[PDB]
Image: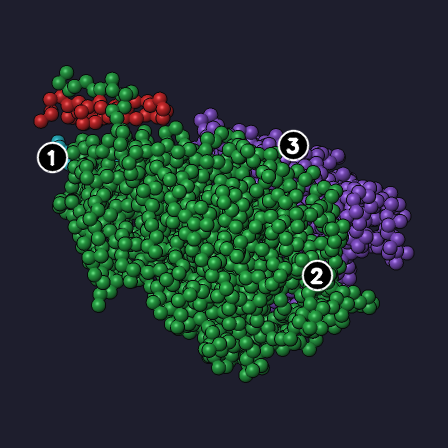
Chain colours: A purple, B green, C cyan, D red
C-alpha cells in the first residue's frame, strides 16, 4: 500500500487499486506528540517503518558573541521548538504508532569557531525574482591599487618583486567586490530585509546594517511597498518569495540569520541501519548537518557536525587549496584577523542538492556556497577597507590539456591574475600564461598573492563571509560572467573548457557508516574542534547554460567582437532569457538528489549496480558508483574527467519546468526510473513587484532514465572509460488547472494521479510506456 | 507451397536483403526467391491515360509474367517450403485464443480459421523484399511487400519516368539565371537610414566613421499592415535583360519533372504502396505457415506528423529580409525549396520557384510584406521519396519499424530520393491488433549536440523549434551491435556550400556559387570563389546601397576581405558596436568592419552543433545528396514508448507577421497539450567517420588512396617533386604566428612548443623570401580609381577619451588566404573546415572529388609537367594553384597529379590534362569529375562483425567501425578495404554489380559482385550518376610575383563557354575515361570480396597522435610517412577476392552456413551418428 | 496463472439437507466465481 | 500431457565451431522433433 501527504500534517494510505483505505488519514504531528506549529518536512521508509522529519514555524534561535554556549534556542518567548525525527509503525488496515523520537539540538561552539562567528556576515537568500543586476556588486580595487597605491602605473614591473608577485602580468586584475552597496550581508544576530536592490552596483547597503536601518530601508519601503501603489524603480519586495523558500517572520520582519540557518538546516532526511542523517535545503546554505545514532536514548540531545570540520576530497590536493586560500588571509599579525582559513577550517557551507541512502551508504551532493574573507578596518586606513577578497581561479590558456592538468593548474591559487587579454583576432578573460611562460619565451616563474599590502599587514582585519549562491566573486566584470556561464575555452587544436575551482563548484560523494560515526564524534567533541575526513567525495565545475542569457549562442575559444561589449560582459549588463522559474541566469541551482538500484542483471558474482540522479539548471546529472567497493566509479587515465559524474542537457520541455516548485523525487525499483514531481501550488503569491501570480496552479512530472554502457554487464564491462549517463524527459503527466495531492506508481505499466480541480477529488489513471504517459479516460471509476 | 526449382534466390536493390539468419528453437533462413525469366518487354504497355491507369496496366501485365516468393530453409541451408502469395489458393489466418494468442501444437502446427487475410486481392500479387523475426514472441515473423512496378521503375517509359535535368552547341549556363540585380529608382526611399548619433551611457571612445544603419519595426493597428517594417525595404529590383531575370518555374520548366504518383494517390491506392504482413511459421509441424495482420504503410501517417514549418518550405524564421536577399541574389528561398529538392513535392518542378511562399511578398507598399497568406507547396511524400523510405525493418518489443533503404529502387542520375523518417507498426493484444505511424528524422535527431561524437566537431547537424534542418538518409541498416541498437549509412547535412552570400553586383563572375544556390548545380562541396562575397550573409537589402560607388569601402556592406577587418580592442568595440543600443522596436547595422573566410563564414551562419539541443540560429538550406557517413546508437525504449501522433505548438510555426517575428526567441516553452519535445533525444551517440578533428583529420585524408589509381592523395613517395592534396605540413613555408595580427599572447597559447612556427601551405603570401613571418598591410585592397584603402584615414581610426587616435586595422596579417589556409591563430583567415573535411572523406572514398581544368588533353591545348608545373614555386603562378574555381580545402594541382590527369599515375602516355595559372591573358576554367561514377547512395547491408564492431559496403570500399560502440584512446576507429575489379571501379553504373554483403563463419565480412549485371547508360552531354553541370570560371591574368597576396579576381563568364568546347566535352564521364586510358573494358570475373585481415592492434595511431614537441598534425604526418609501405597496419588496404562460377544473385544465410545462390547444402557430419530410439522399440 | 499472479476461485458450502458441497451463489453478486489479480484488472 | 502419457522432444547438440547448441536435423526422417506415445499413435 502507498502513502499520500494530504496536507502539512496528515497522511492517507491507498491500496494498489488506487482506492483510499478508510480510517487511514493520520495526523502524525499529533501522533508524534508535537504542537500545532510543527509540520512534516520530509518522509522516508526504512526497515518497513516511516521516518518523519518535523519542524516548527515557531522556532527562535539566538547567537551571543560572548560566552561559551553561543548558539541557543530562545526559551523566553516559546521559541524552544527543536526539530524532530520520528519512527512510526503499523500495528495491524493502517494504524500508526510512534516507536522512537529524536530531537535535533543546536550546534556546539568552540573558542576558535566563535572567533569566526563573532564577525561572520551572510548574504541575503537568492529568490525566484532575484536578477543578475541584484546579485552584481561594484568592482573592487585592482592588484596594483592594493599593493602599490594610486598613480603607481608603469612602475609595476620594478615593484611587483617586493610584494611577491614576481612576473605577474595582471596589474589590472580585480581583488574582489565592494560591500558598501548591493545585497544585504548580515551577522548571525542581525536580520535580513524583505527588499532586494534592482541594481547592486548602485542600490543597497551590503554589510552596512547600520546605514540601511537609519536611511536606506525607509527609501526601500517607499519605492517597493508590500500589499500595488509602488514605483519599484530601485527595489523589489520579495516577502512572499522569501516566505515560499522557508523564511520565518515576526509578522513583516524576518527572524535573525541564525534562526533561518536552523529552520532550513533541518530539511532533508536519510536513514541507514545504524544512523539517521539530516541536512539543509537547496535555497540557502547549511553550515552544519545531523548524524543521529538510532540507538540514542529517549531524551538525549542530538548535536550537528559543522561543515567547517568536514574535510572533503575535492578530487585533487590542489583543488582543496584553491577553495581554502580564498576563505581568508592566514597571518593574524593584527589579533582579531579571524576568518575560516586562519582558524584552520575548511569550506564552511554548502547548498545541499539532497541526501539519500543505498546499501547502508549515505549519498550527498550540492553546490559549494561561496566563501571569502573581507576587510573591517574602520581607520589613514587600509586600501581593501569595506571590500570582499575574491578572484577568478580559471585555468590559464597555456595549460596542459587533460582533466588532472587543467584542475591542478596554479592559475589564481594565492591571488588574482585573470582579466582581459587580446589574442590574435579575438580575446579572453583568462590569463594566457602560467609558469615561466611569456609571449617572448621564458621570463622566470609567475607568482600570485593574497590582496593585502605587506606594509598594512598588522593594521588589517580580514574576517569571514558566506554567499547565497555558488559564486565566490560577484565583482561586476568580464571574467565573472565567463566563469559563471562556462565560456572560458583554450585555443589549442583540441579545444577544452578551462574550469574555475572556486565559482559554481558542484560537490558530491558517498559516506560510510564509520565516516558517519567520525562525523558524530566531531559533533560531541568538547573543547577542540575535531576534524572529519570524507574520502569518497569529488568536486566538478558545473556552470549555468550559456543560452539561458540573451546574447550568447555558442561556447568556443573564438569570441565575436560584440561579446567584448559591456551589455553581455558584466553582471548588471547581462539579460536573462532563462525559463526555469529564476529571474537570474548566472547562479546554478540543484535539487532532488535520489539514488536507486539498477533492476537490470549484472555478471555472476558481482554486486548489483546503483547510481544517483539530481536536477541542475540546464540538465540532469548522474553519479556513478562502484558497488564492489561502495566508492565513486573511477578510471585509470587521469586525462579523462572523473567517470563518477555525467551531465545531459535538457530540451525546452524540461527547461520550461520551474525548478523552485520541486515537490518530490521517487524511484521505481522494477523500472529503474525516477519520477520528479513539480507542484505549481508551491509558487509565491506575488512577484518582486507585488503583482499577484496567475500560474500557481497545476503540476508537471519529469522521467529520468539510465543511458550508456553500465558496469559488470559482461567480461568487457568489468572496468569503464566513459561515464554512464542519464536522460531527463517530460513524462507526459501535466496540468495548469488541477492542484496535485500525489502520484501513485500503481505498477510498472500504470500510474495514478490524485488531484482536486474544484475541492472534490479526482483519480486520473495514465498508461505507462517505459517512462512515457498518456491518460486513460476509460479507467475512470 | 512446395519448393519450386524455377525460383532461385535474389537481392532487392533498395535494402540489399537476400535472406534472414533465423535464430531460436527452429533456426535456418528465410530468403527471397524469384523467377529469372526473360522475354519480358514493358514496351507493350501503351501510355489520354494518366500515370495511375498506366501503372495498373503494367501491374496486370507483370502479374502474369513474374513469380516471387520467400522460401524457408533449414539450419543446413536445405530448402523446406515456398510461401508464394500469388500461387496461394484459399489462404487462412491463425485461430486466435481468448487473449489473441494463436492456437498452436509443436507437431500438429497452427490452427487455421479458413478465412483469407484482409485486402488479400491487392497484396496477392506483391513482391516480398524483406523478412524480420519477433524478438520475444515465438514463430512470429513479418514480411515487407512492395508492388511489382517498384522493381521495374527504371524500365517504365521515359515520358512517365523522367530525369530532373535537360537532354545546337552545348552551353552549361543556358538554364541558369545569371543577370545580377539593379538599383530601383522608384524605391530610393526604401534605403536604410543612417542614425543621427550613438549612445554614450558610460561609453567614452569615438570615431569619424559613418554611423550605424537603423532597422525599425512597429506593429501599430491595421490587420494587414505594420507602422514600420524596415526588413521589408528593398531598394533593388531584378535585371531586365530582354525580360525580368528571375526564378519562374513556368518559363524555366517546360517538360517539368513530376513524381510517378502523388502522396494522396499512394494512400488511396492500397495496391500501389508498401504492405507489412505478420505471419506464423513452425517448419517441423503439419500446418507450418499461417498469416496474421496485413498493414499498409500509409504515406499520410508520415506527412501528418511533419513539423508545421514544412507546409511553407519556401520561407524560414528570418522572414522577409532573407526572402528578399536570396530572391534578388537569384537563389532559392527557405530551408527546403522545391527547385533544389523536387522529390518530396507532389507537383514536382511545377512549384520550382520562389513564388507563393505562404507569406505576402513584393507588395506595392513594402510595410504589407511578411504577413501570413495562402500557400500550396508543402513537403510531402510522393512515389520516389516514398519507396526510398521502404526497407530495413527492426522488431523491438511489440513494434516493427521501417527505417528505409538507400533509394536505389527509384534513384535517377539527376535525382536523390532518400528516407525522410521512420515508420512504426505497433502491435497489441498478442499481435492481433495493429497501429501504423511515421516520424520524421528531423524530430528524432533534434537532440544532437557536439559532446555525442569523438570525431569532427561543429558539423552542420543542428536545428531549431521550426525544424529547418531536414535530415534524409541512404540507410545501411538498423541492427543490435551487442547491447546497442545501431542505425548506419550516409546522411544529408545542412548546407555549407551556399552559406556565403554574393554582393548584388558579382553574380555573373561567380557562376558556380549562383548555380549551386539555384539548384542547377547539385554539388554539395564548397567551391572556392570568394572575391565577390558580401562581408556578412545576414545584411538586409536596405543596407546594400549605403556605399554604391565603393569609395568609403561600405562599412556595413562591402566585398568580404579579412584584411580590412577591425580590432577587438575595447575602444574599437565601444565606438563601433556597444555604442549602438538595440531596443524592443529597433535593431542596428553596425559600422564595424566584419569579414572572414570559409571557416569564419560557417562559424557564424551555419547550423553547427553546440552543447545544447535545437540551438541553430541559422540553417541555410539542405544538401542535395547524402554528404556524410553516419552511425548512431538509438534509444530503443524511447522508440517503443513514444506516441503514434506527434503534436506541435504555435512555437513550431513561423510568426504570422514581421512585428511578432522581430523579437522572436530561438527557444520557447512547449504548450502543455503538445508532445513534440519528447521525440528529440532518440540518438544517444553518433559517429561520422574516424575519431579525429581539424588539421589532424587532413593528414589521414592524404594517407588514403584513390580507388581508380590505388595511389595516395599525399603523392609522398618520390625540389619539383609532387606535393599532397589535403595537408599543409612541409608544404609552403614556416611562418611565425607570434608576428601575426596583434602580435601579443600567442607563443604558448596555440602551440605547446617554444617555436610558434606553422606551415603556410600552397599558394602563400610573403613580403620576401627572407620575411616569412607575417605579411604587413601591403596586400591592401584598392577600389576602382583613387583606388587604395586608407588605414590612418579619419573613418578608419578610433579616438578614446584623451585623444590617442589609433587605427582599427591589424599591422601584419597571416601568410596565406588560399583554399588550403589553416590558421590555428586566425579563424578569419582559415578556409579549411570540419564540414568540408567530412564531405571530402566520403567523396575521396567514392573517388568523385572534382578537379579545375584549363587545358584538355587535345592538340594546341595541352598541359606539360616540366616547365609548366613547378612544385618549388608554389607562392607564384608556377605552382598552378587556381585560387578561384576549385574545391575548397585542397590543392587542385596535387589532386590532378593523384588522378593522373597529368603524369603516369593513370595512363602510361601522359593525358596532358591540367590547370595553368596564366600570366599572359585572362583564364577560362571548368571543374570536371574523376571519370568515376560512385554515388553517396551506394550504401549496402549493415554487417555486425562482433559485439563491439560493425560495417558496410560504401562504393568501392568496405568501411568498418572499430571504435564507436566502445572507443579506445589512440585509435582511428575505421578500417577500409577497397575492391580490386577495375571494370567495376570504372563502370558507368558501378553499383549495379553489388549483390549484398554478409558476415562469414570465419568471422570476416564478405561482399558479392557480379560484373555481368553492370547496367549500361541509356545514352551533347551524357548523363551518368556522377554528372554535374559545372559552370565556367573566368579570371584576370595571374601575377608573376606576389600572386596570392590578394583574393584572385574573376571577370564576367556569361559569354565564356563558347571558347571552352574541349573542356566542356570532359563534363561527360565517358570522355574523361577515354583520355585516362579507361575508355572501354581494357576485365573481370564474378565472385566474393573479403575484408583486409585485422588484429586488435590495427589502427593504433597513438604514437602519431598527441605531443607538443611537434603539433598533433605534424606528428601524425611524420607517422603516416613512416607507414606508407605498410598501410595494412593502420587498417587501409585491398580486399581479397575469391572467384565464383556463374551468376551471383544472392546468399542464403543460416546461423551455421552462408550459401551463395543456396548451393552446397550438406547433412552435417557431426550429428550423423546421433538419432532417436524408434517408438516401436 | 503463475506469471500473471491471477487466481480464479468458486466458493462452496456444505448444505445440511443434502450432504453435497453446493456453490455460494451470492458470494460476488454476479455468481460464485471471482478473480484475484493485481493492477492488470485493466483488461 | 500427463493423462495421455505423451512426450514431445527436440534433440540438441553442442557445435564445436559456433560454441552454442544446435538441433540434430537427422534425428528422425522428418526433423529434430519426435513424440513418445504409449500406443495412442491413432
Q: Quadrant of the N terminus of chain A?
A: top left
Which callout, 2 or 1, points to the residue nearer the camera? 2
Q: In the picture provided, is A653 more to the left or to the right than C21?
A: right
Residue that appears at 23% across and 63% down: B47
Would you name the residue on which mark 1 appears?
A: C17
Q: Residue B840: where, in percent of width, then height?
A: 52, 49
Mark 2 = which residue? B779
Give residue A568's quadrant in the image: bottom right
- Chain ID, mark 2: B
Distance between the alpha carbons at the discs numbered 2 and 3: 72 Å
- Residue count near mark 2 (Cα–Cα under 10 Å), binned few <14, some 14–19, many ≥20: some
In x, y percent, where is residue A673?
45, 43
Q: Secondary structure at mark 3?
A: helix
Nearer the camera: disc 2 or disc 3? 2
Q: Is residue A702 above or below residue A87?
A: below
Q: Tell me the tag on residue A592.
A: none
In the depicted structure, whether residue B149 falls above or below residue A413: below
Name the residue beneath numbered marker 3. Answer: A518
Mark 3 vs mark 1: in front: 3
Instruction: Decide if residue A580 is in sight here.
Output: no
Q: Chain of mark 1?
A: C
Q: Residue at x 76, y 38 (%)?
A: A344
- Residue placed most toward the observer, B409 or A664: B409
Residue A210 drawn above or below residue C25: below
> Is B684 in front, or is A17?
B684
Image marks 2 and 1: residues in contact by CB distance under 8 Å? no
Q: Are marks 2 and 1 on the same chain?
A: no
Amino acid at each position: 500500500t502507498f502513502l499520500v501527504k494530504e496536507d502539512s500534517k496528515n497522511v492517507t494510505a491507498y491500496t494498489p487499486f488506487a482506492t483510499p483505505i478508510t480510517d487511514s488519514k493520520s495526523d502524525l504531528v499529533s501522533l508524534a506528540q508535537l504542537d500545532s506549529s510543527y509540520q512534516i518536512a520530509d518522509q522516508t521508509i526504512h526497515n518497513t517503518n516511516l521516518f518523519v522529519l518535523f519542524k516548527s514555524r515557531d522556532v527562535k534561535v539566538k547567537y551571543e558573541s560572548s560566552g561559551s554556549n553561543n548558539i541557543s534556542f530562545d526559551s523566553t518567548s516559546q521559541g524552544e521548538k527543536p526539530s524532530y525525527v520520528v519512527e512510526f509503525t503499523n500495528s495491524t488496515g493502517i494504524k500508526w504508532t510512534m516507536v522512537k523520537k529524536y530531537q535535533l539540538d543546536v550546534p556546539n561552539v568552540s573558542s576558535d569557531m566563535n572567533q569566526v562567528l563573532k564577525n561572520l556576515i551572510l548574504e541575503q537568500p537568492l529568490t525566484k525574482y532575484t536578477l543578475n543586476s541584484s546579485l552584481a556588486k561594484e568592482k573592487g580595487k585592482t592588484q596594483r591599487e592594493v599593493h602599490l597605491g594610486s598613480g603607481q602605473a608603469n612602475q609595476w614591473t620594478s615593484q611587483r618583486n617586493q610584494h611577491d608577485l614576481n612576473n605577474n602580468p595582471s596589474p589590472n586584475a580585480s581583488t574582489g567586490f565592494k560591500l558598501t552597496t548591493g545585497n544585504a550581508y548580515r551577522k548571525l544576530s542581525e536580520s535580513w530585509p524583505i527588499y532586494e536592490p534592482i541594481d547592486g552596483t548602485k542600490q543597497g547597503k551590503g554589510k552596512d546594517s547600520s546605514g540601511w536601518s537609519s536611511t536606506e530601508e525607509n527609501e526601500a519601503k517607499n519605492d517597493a511597498p508590500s500589499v500595488s501603489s509602488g514605483t519599484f524603480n530601485k527595489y523589489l519586495n520579495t516577502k512572499q518569495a522569501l516566505e515560499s523558500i522557508g523564511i520565518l517572520f515576526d509578522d513583516q520582519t524576518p527572524r535573525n540569520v541564525i534562526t533561518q540557518l536552523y529552520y532550513a538546516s533541518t530539511s532533508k532526511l536519510a536513514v541507514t541501519n545504524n544512523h539517521i542523517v539530516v541536512m539543509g535545503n537547496s535555497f540557502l546554505p547549511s553550515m552544519w548537518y545531523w548524524v543521529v545514532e538510532r540507538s540514542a536514548q529517549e531524551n538525549a540531545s542530538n548535536k550537528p557536525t559543522w561543515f567547517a570540520n568536514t574535510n572533503l576530497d575535492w578530487g585533487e590536493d590542489k583543488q582543496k587549496q584553491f577553495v581554502e586560500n580564498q576563505l581568508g588571509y592566514k597571518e593574524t599579525t593584527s589579533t582579531n584577523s579571524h576568518n575560516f582559513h586562519s582558524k584552520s577550517f575548511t569550506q564552511p557551507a554548502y547548498l545541499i542538492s539532497g541526501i539519500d541512502s543505498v546499501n547502508d551508504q549515505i549519498i550527498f551532493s550540492g553546490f559549494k556556497a561561496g566563501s571569502v574573507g573581507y576587510d573591517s578596518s574602520s581607520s589613514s586606513s587600509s586600501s581593501t577597507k569595506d571590500q570582499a577578497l575574491a578572484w577568478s581561479t580559471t585555468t590559464s590558456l597555456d595549460s596542459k590539456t587533460g582533466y588532472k592538468d587543467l584542475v591542478t593548474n596554479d592559475t589564481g591559487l594565492n591571488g588574482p591574475i585573470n582579466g582581459s587579454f587580446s589574442i590574435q583576432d579575438t580575446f579572453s578573460f583568462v590569463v594566457p600564461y602560467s609558469g615561466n611562460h611569456t609571449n617572448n619565451g621564458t621570463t622566470g616563474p609567475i607568482k600570485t598573492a593574497y590582496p593585502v599590502k605587506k606594509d598594512q599587514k598588522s593594521t588589517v582585519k580580514i574576517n569571514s563571509l558566506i554567499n547565497a549562491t555558488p559564486l565566490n566573486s560577484y565583482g561586476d566584470e568580464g571574467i565573472g560572467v565567463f566563469d559563471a556561464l562556462g565560456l572560458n575555452y583554450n585555443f589549442k587544436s583540441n579545444q577544452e573548457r578551462l574550469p574555475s575551482r572556486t565559482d559554481q563548484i558542484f560537490v558530491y560523494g558517498i559516506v560510510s557508516p564509520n565516516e558517519l560515526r567520525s562525523a558524530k564524534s566531531s559533533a560531541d567533541s568538547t573543547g577542540s574542534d575535531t576534524k572529519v575526513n570524507w574520502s569518497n567525495t569529488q568536486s566538478r565545475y558545473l556552470p549555468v547554460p550559456y543560452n539561458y542569457s540573451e546574447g550568447i549562442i555558442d561556447a568556443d575559444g573564438f569570441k565575436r567582437p560584440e561579446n567584448r561589449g559591456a551589455s553581455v560582459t558584466t553582471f548588471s549588463g547581462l539579460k536573462s532569457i532563462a525559463p526555469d522559474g529564476f529571474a537570474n541566469s548566472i547562479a546554478n541551482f540543484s535539487v532532488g538528489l535520489k539514488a536507486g538500484i539498477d533492476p537490470n542483471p549484472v555478471m555472476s558474482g558481482k554486486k548489483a549496480n546503483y547510481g544517483a540522479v539530481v536536477l541542475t539548471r540546464g540538465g540532469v546529472v548522474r553519479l556513478n558508483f562502484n558497488p564492489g567497493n561502495d566508492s565513486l566509479l573511477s578510471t585509470t587515465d587521469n586525462n579523462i574527467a572523473p567517470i563518477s559524474f555525467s551531465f545531459t542537457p535538457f530540451t525546452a520541455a524540461e527547461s520550461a519546468v520551474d525548478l523552485t516548485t520541486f515537490k518530490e523525487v521517487t524511484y521505481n525499483q522494477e523500472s529503474g526510473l525516477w519520477s520528479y514531481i513539480f507542484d505549481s501550488s508551491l509558487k509565491p503569491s506575488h512577484d518582486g513587484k507585488q503583482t499577484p501570480v496567475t500560474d500557481n496552479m497545476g503540476f508537471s512530472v519529469i522521467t529520468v532514465s539510465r543511458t550508456g554502457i553500465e558496469l559488470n554487464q559482461d567480461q568487457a564491462t568489468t572496468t569503464l572509460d566513459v561515464a554512464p549517463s542519464a536522460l531527463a524527459v517530460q513524462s507526459g503527466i501535466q496540468s495548469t488547472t488541477q492542484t496535485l495531492t500525489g502520484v501513485l506508481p500503481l505498477s510498472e505499466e500504470f500510474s495514478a494521479v490524485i488531484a482536486k480541480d474544484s475541492d472534490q477529488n479526482k483519480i486520473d489513471i495514465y498508461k505507462n510506456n517505459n517512462g512515457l504517459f498518456e491518460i486513460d479516460t476509460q479507467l475512470s471509476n | 507451397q512446395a519448393v519450386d526449382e524455377t525460383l532461385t534466390p535474389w537481392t532487392w536493390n533498395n535494402n540489399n536483403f537476400s535472406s534472414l539468419k533465423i535464430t531460436g528453437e527452429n533456426p535456418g533462413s528465410f530468403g527471397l526467391v524469384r523467377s529469372q525469366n526473360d522475354n519480358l518487354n514493358i514496351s507493350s504497355v501503351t501510355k489520354s491515360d494518366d500515370n495511375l491507369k498506366y501503372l495498373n496496366a503494367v501491374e496486370k501485365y507483370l502479374d502474369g509474367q513474374q513469380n516471387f516468393a520467400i522460401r524457408r530453409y533449414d539450419n543446413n541451408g536445405r530448402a523446406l517450403y515456398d510461401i508464394n502469395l500469388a500461387k496461394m489458393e484459399n489462404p487462412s489466418t491463425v485461430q486466435r485464443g481468448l487473449n489473441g494468442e494463436p492456437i498452436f501444437d509443436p507437431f500438429k502446427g497452427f490452427g487455421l480459421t479458413g478465412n483469407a487475410p484482409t485486402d488479400w486481392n491487392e497484396i496477392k500479387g506483391k513482391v516480398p523484399v524483406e523478412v524480420v523475426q519477433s524478438p520475444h514472441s515465438p514463430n512470429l515473423y513479418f514480411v515487407l511487400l512492395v508492388p511489382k512496378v517498384a522493381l521495374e521503375y527504371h524500365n517504365l517509359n521515359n515520358q512517365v519516368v523522367k530525369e530532373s535535368l535537360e537532354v545546337s552547341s552545348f552551353n552549361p549556363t543556358q538554364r541558369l539565371q545569371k543577370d545580377s540585380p539593379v538599383k530601383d529608382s522608384s524605391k530610393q526611399g526604401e534605403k536604410l537610414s543612417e542614425t543621427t548619433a550613438s549612445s554614450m551611457s558610460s561609453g567614452m571612445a569615438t570615431s569619424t566613421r559613418a554611423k550605424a544603419l537603423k532597422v525599425e519595426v512597429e506593429r501599430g493597428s491595421q490587420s494587414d499592415s505594420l507602422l514600420k517594417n524596415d526588413f521589408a525595404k528593398k531598394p533593388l529590383k531584378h535585371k531586365n535583360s530582354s525580360g525580368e531575370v528571375k526564378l519562374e518555374a513556368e518559363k524555366e520548366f517546360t517538360e517539368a519533372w513530376k513524381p510517378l504518383l502523388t502522396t494522396d494517390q499512394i494512400a488511396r491506392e492500397k495496391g500501389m504502396g508498401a504492405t507489412v504482413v505478420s505471419f506464423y511459421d513452425a517448419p517441423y509441424s503439419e500446418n507450418h505457415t499461417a498469416f496474421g495482420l496485413v498493414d499498409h504503410i500509409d504515406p499520410k501517417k508520415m506527412v501528418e506528423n511533419y513539423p508545421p514549418s514544412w507546409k511553407t518550405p519556401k520561407w524560414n524564421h528570418h522572414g522577409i529580409w532573407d526572402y528578399n536577399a536570396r530572391n534578388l541574389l537569384l537563389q532559392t528561398t527557405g530551408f527546403f525549396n522545391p527547385r533544389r529538392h523536387p522529390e518530396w513535392f507532389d507537383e514536382g518542378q511545377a512549384k520550382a520557384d520562389n513564388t507563393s511562399p505562404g507569406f505576402k511578398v513584393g507588395d506595392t507598399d513594402h510595410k504589407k510584406d511578411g504577413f501570413k497568406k495562402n500557400s500550396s507547396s508543402p513537403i510531402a511524400l510522393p512515389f520516389e521519396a516514398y519507396f526510398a523510405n521502404i526497407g530495413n525493418m527492426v522488431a523491438i518489443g511489440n513494434s516493427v519499424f521501417i527505417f528505409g533503404g538507400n533509394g536505389h529502387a527509384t534513384k535517377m542520375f539527376t535525382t536523390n530520393p532518400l528516407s525522410i523518417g521512420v515508420f512504426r507498426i505497433k502491435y497489441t493484444d498478442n499481435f492481433s491488433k495493429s497501429s501504423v505511424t511515421g516520424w520524421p528524422y528531423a524530430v528524432l535527431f533534434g537532440g544532437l549536440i557536439n559532446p555525442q561524437t569523438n570525431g569532427l566537431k561543429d558539423l552542420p547537424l543542428g536545428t531549431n523549434r521550426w525544424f529547418e534542418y531536414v535530415p534524409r538518409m541512404a540507410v545501411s541498416g538498423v541492427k543490435w551491435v551487442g547491447n546497442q541498437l545501431v542505425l548506419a549509412g550516409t546522411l544529408t547535412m545542412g548546407d555549407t556550400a551556399t552559406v556565403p552570400r554574393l554582393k548584388y553586383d558579382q553574380l555573373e563572375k561567380h557562376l558556380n556559387l549562383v548555380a549551386q544556390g539555384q539548384g542547377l548545380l547539385r554539388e554539395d562541396l564548397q567551391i572556392f570563389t570568394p572575391y565577390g562575397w558580401a562581408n556578412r550573409p545576414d545584411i538586409p537589402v536596405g543596407a546594400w546601397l549605403q556605399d554604391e560607388m565603393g569609395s568609403k569601402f561600405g562599412p556595413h556592406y562591402f566585398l568580404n576581405n579579412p584584411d580590412i577587418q577591425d580590432n577587438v580592442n575595447n575602444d574599437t568595440v565601444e565606438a563601433l558596436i556597444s555604442s549602438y543600443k538595440n531596443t524592443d522596436k529597433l535593431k542596428h547595422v553596425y559600422p564595424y568592419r566584419y569579414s572572414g573566410l570559409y571557416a569564419w563564414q560557417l562559424f557564424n551562419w551555419s547550423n553547427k552543433l553546440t552543447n545544447t539541443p535545437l540551438s541553430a540560429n541559422f540553417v541555410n538550406e539542405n544538401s542535395y545528396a547524402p554528404n556524410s557517413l553516419f552511425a548512431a546508437i538509438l534509444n530503443e525504449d524511447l522508440l517503443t514508448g513514444l506516441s503514434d501522433k506527434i503534436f506541435y505548438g504555435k512555437e513550431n510555426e513561423f510568426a504570422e507577421n514581421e512585428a511578432d517575428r522581430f523579437n522572436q526567441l530561438l527557444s520557447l516553452n512547449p504548450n502543455p497539450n503538445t508532445n513534440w519535445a519528447r521525440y528529440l533525444n532518440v540518438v544517444q551517440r553518433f559517429t561520422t567517420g574516424p575519431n579525429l578533428d581539424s588539421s589532424t583529420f587532413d593528414q589521414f585524408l592524404d594517407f588514403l588512396p584513390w580507388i581508380g589509381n590505388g595511389k595516395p592523395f599525399s603523392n609522398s613517395p618520390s625540389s619539383s617533386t609532387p606535393l599532397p592534396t589535403f595537408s599543409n605540413i612541409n608544404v609552403g613555408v614556416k611562418s611565425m604566428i607570434t608576428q601575426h595580427l596583434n602580435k601579443e599572447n600567442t607563443r604558448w597559447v596555440f602551440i605547446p612548443n617554444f617555436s610558434p612556427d606553422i606551415w603556410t601551405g600552397a599558394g602563400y603570401r610573403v613580403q620576401s623570401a627572407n620575411q616569412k613571418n607575417g605579411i604587413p598591410f601591403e596586400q591592401v585592397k584598392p577600389s576602382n580609381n583613387s583606388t587604395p584603402f586608407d588605414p590612418n584615414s579619419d573613418d578608419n581610426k578610433v579616438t578614446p577619451s584623451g585623444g590617442s587616435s589609433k587605427p582599427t586595422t591589424y599591422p601584419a596579417l597571416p601568410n596565406s588566404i588560399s583554399p588550403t589556409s589553416d590558421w590555428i591563430n586566425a579563424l578569419t583567415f582559415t578556409n579549411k573546415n570540419n564540414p568540408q573535411r567530412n564531405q571530402l572523406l566520403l567523396r575521396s572514398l567514392l573517388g568523385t572529388i572534382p578537379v579545375l581544368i584549363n587545358k584538355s588533353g587535345d592538340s594546341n591545348d595541352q598541359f606539360n609537367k616540366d616547365s609548366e608545373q613547378k612544385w618549388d614555386k608554389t607562392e607564384t603562378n608556377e605552382g598552378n594553384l587556381p585560387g578561384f574555381g576549385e574545391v575548397n580545402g585542397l590543392y587542385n594541382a596535387a589532386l590532378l597529379h593523384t588522378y593522373g590527369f597529368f603524369g603516369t599515375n593513370t595512363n602510361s602516355t601522359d593525358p596532358k590534362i591540367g590547370f595553368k595559372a596564366d600570366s599572359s591573358s585572362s583564364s577560362s576554367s571548368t571543374l570536371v569529375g574523376s571519370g568515376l561514377n560512385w554515388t553517396s547512395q551506394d550504401v549496402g547491408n549493415l554487417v555486425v562483425i562482433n559485439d563491439t564492431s560493425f560495417g558496410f559496403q560504401l562504393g568501392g570500399w568496405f568501411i568498418t567501425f572499430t571504435d564507436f560502440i566502445r572507443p579506445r584512446t589512440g585509435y582511428l576507429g575505421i578500417t577500409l578495404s577497397s575492391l580490386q575489379d577495375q571494370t567495376i571501379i570504372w563502370a558507368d553504373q558501378p553499383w549495379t554489380s553489388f549483390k549484398g554483403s554478409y558476415l562469414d563463419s570465419d568471422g570476416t565480412p564478405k561482399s558479392l559482385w557480379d560484373p555481368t549485371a553492370l547496367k549500361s547508360l541509356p545514352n551533347n552531354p551524357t548523363l551518368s550518376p556522377s554528372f554535374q553541370l559545372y559552370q565556367p570560371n573566368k579570371v584576370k591574368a595571374y601575377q608573376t610575383t606576389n600572386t596570392y597576396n590578394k583574393l584572385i579576381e574573376p571577370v564576367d563568364a556569361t559569354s565564356a563557354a563558347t571558347n571552352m568546347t574541349s573542356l566542356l566535352k570532359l563534363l561527360t564521364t565517358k570522355n574523361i575515361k577515354a583520355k585516362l586510358g579507361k575508355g572501354t573494358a581494357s576485365n573481370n570475373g564474378g565472385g566474393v570480396s573479403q575484408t583486409i585481415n585485422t588484429i586488435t592492434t590495427t589502427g593504433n595511431i597513438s604514437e602519431g597522435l598527441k605531443e607538443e614537441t611537434s603539433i598533433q598534425a605534424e606528428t601524425l604526418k611524420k607517422f603516416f610517412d613512416s607507414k606508407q609501405n605498410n598501410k595494412s597496419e593502420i587498417g587501409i588496404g585491398d580486399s581479397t577476392f575469391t572467384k565464383m562460377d556463374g551468376k551471383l544473385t544472392g546468399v542464403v544465410s543460416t546461423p551455421l552456413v552462408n550459401l551463395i545462390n543456396g548451393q552446397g547444402a550438406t547433412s552435417d557430419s557431426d550429428t550423423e551418428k546421433i538419432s532417436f530410439k524408434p517408438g516401436n522399440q | 496463472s503463475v506469471e500473471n499472479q491471477t487466481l480464479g476461485v468458486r466458493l462452496e458450502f456444505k448444505d445440511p439437507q443434502t450432504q453435497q458441497f453446493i456453490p455460494v451463489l451470492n458470494a460476488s453478486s454476479t455468481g460464485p466465481q471471482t478473480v484475484f489479480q493485481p493492477f492488470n484488472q485493466w483488461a
